[PDB]
Length: 220
Length: 223
Ligand SMILES: O=C(c1cc(Cl)c(O)cc1O)N1CCC[C@@H]1c1ccc(CN2CCC(F)(F)C2)cc1
Ligand SMILES: O=C(c1cc(Cl)c(O)cc1O)N1CCC[C@@H]1c1ccc(CN2CCC(F)(F)C2)cc1
Image: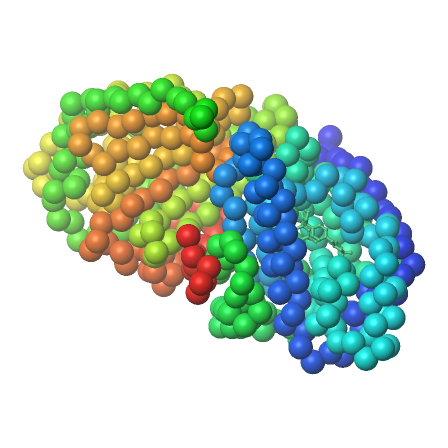
């Protein structure tokens, strides 16, 4: 008689990816703010892909025409959420894209960090998503692709991640990254901080970026 | 070559007394216009109760979203205040029947109590609370989505008529979204501090999460 029941799948990260996450999540780095640049850049890439699909098949935008990125800090939850209405990811995409298949750059980037490369270059090796763990103890990715159901990926590192169908609020289409911030990284929940980081690092992104400051009202 | 969309747009006349009530609401001063938010939050709470009670005996009714809540979104750039809930929503007929074509006994007497000069606050008791929206809004748009039906848009600028159409905007899972296009001298209801105090004052007993999202477009990234 449960309110609900669903299957949860747990997957091991590919060895190199686990190594990178441990390196990122544990090691001191001076400008972690670049995490937000990498996630906005990923969102922009997703919006490009749906935009170009719609040019040959407009019905692809039946799930929503607006192409944009929302940034949603929630001090009460200590979460920062980046939402886009891009092309989204199938379940296979989540499992493949986000853990089980290490690409050249995974090892290549740890290879480069030894060679004197910087962490802000994590994006040039195509593994920018993982910079999220510079500031987050846990990351949840919720995604909805056309013709597919809405899935939720999550990891606190430690070598594994889970995937399940998301029963939360339905998205029309796109991807939402929920960063559950480390205790000492709450600065990234502040309007002034988010504003300056976007102005500094994401000036060239070609889609609306909008802030929604979230506050749960007292007693509610 | 081909249109993106093609749809019928229907225009309805407001029932006579409803039209009369709206004109009174728009053209009369009241010292406590803030009660409009109480009325719309109350309507959302009712819608939420209904999908919850339905879900008891029929659990699959929450397939369109499990979370039951109310969001308030002020957008200073657009001068809109939006109230969104994940309640049971309205079918096209519910929308037409509820929002303007049928008048109840509680209209002619209330609308006459205001012509007589009563306190606008009593509007909710007479079951016409939605129309308090026009205390602060020059136009109201309602987007609604009921299980097993299409998403519809209702809209009126209170000229004696309103329109209904299938909506082609951003998809809602389920529920109702009220978009208030605010009057120029009623923009205070876009302010965070103002919204907080109104909710704290009038909606203390609403048994659902009410969440404010202060919308701010970022420099060089508008639209
Ligand atoms: O839905 C998303 C998406 C993904 C993330 Cl993570 C996001 O923050 C926002 C998004 O909209 N897509 C769909 C197609 C393009 C975009 C995407 C998909 C995969 C990568 C590669 N990275 C994934 C982990 C990695 F190993 F670091 C390498 C980048 C962008
Ligand atoms: O979708 C909604 C809903 C409607 C409005 Cl307006 C809202 O602000 C939020 C909502 O969720 N429903 C579904 C069922 C219960 C709820 C509802 C429906 C009708 C009335 C009566 N009013 C309609 C005009 C009136 F004449 F003033 C009397 C109240 C609540």
